[PDB]
Amino acid sequence: EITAISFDEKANLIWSGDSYGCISSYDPTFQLYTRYRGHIGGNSVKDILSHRDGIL
Amino acid sequence: SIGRQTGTVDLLDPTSNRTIKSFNAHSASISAMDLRDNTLVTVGKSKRFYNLYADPFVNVYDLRTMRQLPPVSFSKGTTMGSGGADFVQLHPLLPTVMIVASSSGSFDFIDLSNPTLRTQYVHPCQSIKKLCLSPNGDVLGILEADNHLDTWRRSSNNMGMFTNTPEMLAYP
Amino acid sequence: NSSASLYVGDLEPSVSEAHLYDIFSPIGSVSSIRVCRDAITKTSLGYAYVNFNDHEAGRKAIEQLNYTPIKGRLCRIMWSQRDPSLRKKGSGNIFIKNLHPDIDNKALYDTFSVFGDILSSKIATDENGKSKGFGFVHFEEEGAAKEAIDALNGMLLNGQEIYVAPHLSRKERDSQLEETKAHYTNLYVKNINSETTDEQFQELFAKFGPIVSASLEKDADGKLKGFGFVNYEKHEDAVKAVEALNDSELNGEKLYVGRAQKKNERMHVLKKQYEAYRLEKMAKYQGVNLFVKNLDDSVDDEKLEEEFAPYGTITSAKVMRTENGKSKGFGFVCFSTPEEATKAITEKNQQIVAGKPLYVAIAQRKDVRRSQLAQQIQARNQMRYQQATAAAAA
Amino acid sequence: ENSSASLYVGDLEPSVSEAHLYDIFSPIGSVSSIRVCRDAITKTSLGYAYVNFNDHEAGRKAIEQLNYTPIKGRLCRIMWSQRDPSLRKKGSGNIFIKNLHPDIDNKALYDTFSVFGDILSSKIATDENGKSKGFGFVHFEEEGAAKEAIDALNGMLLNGQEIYV
């Protein structure tokens, strides 16, 4: 259901959005770090990007 | 850049905000575009309905003096259909060298200047949703809806991604 | 009631707190060393502080080590409890002046400790021991200092008096060398009529500085230059008639009094010229000039002026070279037009003139240091990311 | 200034990219950022690169592993970074030589000649299978180490060829 992907420039995390509502960060090869929402509802996310300070 | 409804690119200044150039990359779509060091890569489809025709050429443009750089043709890989260069992405540390990848995954580490120097890494697995990069230059991330990554490169590091400063590293 | 928190002044950058610990570790109670690396670029403020758990060992380390050479420079270790109050009071280092140029804080400290423990003692002891013959000595407080004033004002000390009565400015060993009865900065009065004689240079001028020597300056050409040297008593009266008798009337004619042969005890004339150059030195352009670097070598002021002829009134075309030989990239055209310079920001920035591109920025030696600050920033940043990488890389 | 790498290659090419460049010193670790900033109407050589690493010590480490070995005729030049107060930093001139010895390289040149004078740019004409072309430009930080190396031995006899001012 994964619908948007980006990195972070400062860690080994992955930043994924499924089709459930969420946005998650991921450790190396098979481990998650966080999964939060900044999303209202419906589908999760159009797109994801990295930044100097955080994740948009 | 404005990758637009009809495969075209209106390029503008965020500062002066006068229209200077309405380039026309394709006629139908614009899907895979990057702007790095006054160089522009784009591939979208250009055929309307019976198409299967994500365009079999990497359309290369520059920001230097408004010129169509010679478009590198994209092969059909191994399959019998069209080329389909729907994933074209310049390298982070090498802002002209790119990676071009199809829907099934015929990805190639490829120069901008010399198209002969191609590294046509085949994909002995299932077709993709998306793929991402390597700021450490040695990380293939193929990602479908399966949540199972694999990197294909030589084993320069035991590391995954770039950097190692986590604010809750292994212990909150 | 602090145990000990002690002033250590007139330092040199070799003395770290490791070296201070190696000095004061056989004193007995080492608490801490506040090296005053002030937070601009770790510079000393001229001093530092050492804190001791023992008040007695602190008094010990003062009275043993006051102008003793810690790594080759004499240690100005005193009290500074009232010294932030001397900071935000204006008081502190008073002007016990005409000191001795061969006696430092240690010998005069142990000499006039009968006048008191000098809480703010300095002589002009720069240059690894050389005093210029004066300094800012001040005792405990007003009573001990006034006791030293009323007890010793004009006494003998190796054939030299002291002067705390007046706030005597620098060059005091060579004060009488300035006061020597032959040399003096005269006053050239320009465009004098021939009516002024040696009598006339003493009439209205001896009040503004007494004159015996009054010379109607004829030149080596027989005539008058119109410039006559007024020989007052002191260079301050040279000041008084350069900025009080300026274009004045002696009888009926001008007194354009300039300083005939300045002896440097009054100074800073045209140093504002410097700041006038600060209108155009590091804030270079005033949106007018163009630091155009990276020409061709065939691009002289010839081809620079040739390119900038459509770009307004050219006033200064100038390329510095290896002694009018090899330029290492850069020229300048001071314009007279700012909007043609904006047209060059459009055009002549990102411009091939011959084969190699023009480079346009405002010309400063100022923020080279700020760029080095940014280099420090990025250096500590890559150090930090490498520290995190080597930490979590296991 | 320039406490970091700032590793400055000059005397550049029109149309050879940084691709094989990054191919060669890949296994060294610290390769931070490589870029040639450019003019707008300019697909010819202009003359400044930035093979930037993290710190200066990574540049010296890149020297100390292996440096100045011939591939594609180009040899990577070192950090200069020297602008309009440097009218004569590396422009205080050089000995220009007619009849250098025809075996004079740059590496053994500065290796034996690190004693008297520090050579900045030994702009030496070496071509056609190990042959210094007689004319060269041995270049310094001043014109004083130049005179030091001349007055020591302005060249010497190893196969006899003294060099020129």
Image (cartoon, coloured by chain):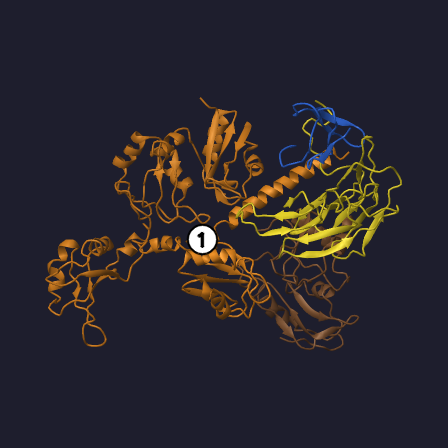
Residue D51 visible at all: no
| Relative to D139, B53 lies left or right | right
Pick the quarter of the image with the C terminus of chain B: top right
Quadrant of the image occupied by residue C358: bottom right
- Is B47 situated left or right of C342 in this image? right
Residue closer to the observer: C174 or A16: A16
Classify residue A54 by image quadrant: top right
Label 1, on which residue? C282
Q: Where is residue D61 in the image (x, y as percent from the top left)?
A: 72, 51
Instruction: Kindly identify the residue that appears in the image at 18 percent across and 72 percent down.
Output: C224
Q: Camera-side residue: C256 or C325?
A: C325
Q: Which sits in the foreground, C267 or C298?
A: C298
**Picture residue at 58% right of the left edge, 43% below the top:** C376
Q: In this view, does D51 lie above or below D149?
A: above
Q: Which amino acid does label 1 sit on?
A: Met
Q: Is residue D25 left or right of residue C99?
A: right
Q: The orange chain is which one?
A: C
Badge 1, how many Cα within 10 Å: few under 14, some, many 20+?
A: some
Chain ID for brown: D
- Residue B162 horizontal/vertical position (percent): 73, 39
> From what the image shows, is residue B155 above or below residue C217?
above
The colour assigned to chain B within the rendered structure:
yellow
- Residue furthest out toward the front: B49
Question: In front: B154, or B122?
Answer: B122
For the image, the number of numbered tags is: 1
Question: Mark 1, chain letter?
Answer: C
Letter of the blue chain: A
Q: Identify the element where label 1 is drawn.
A: loop
The answer to which quarter of the image holds residue A25 is top right
Instruction: Name the side, left or right, on which C277 lies relative to C48.
Output: left
Residue C381 showing in the rendered view: yes
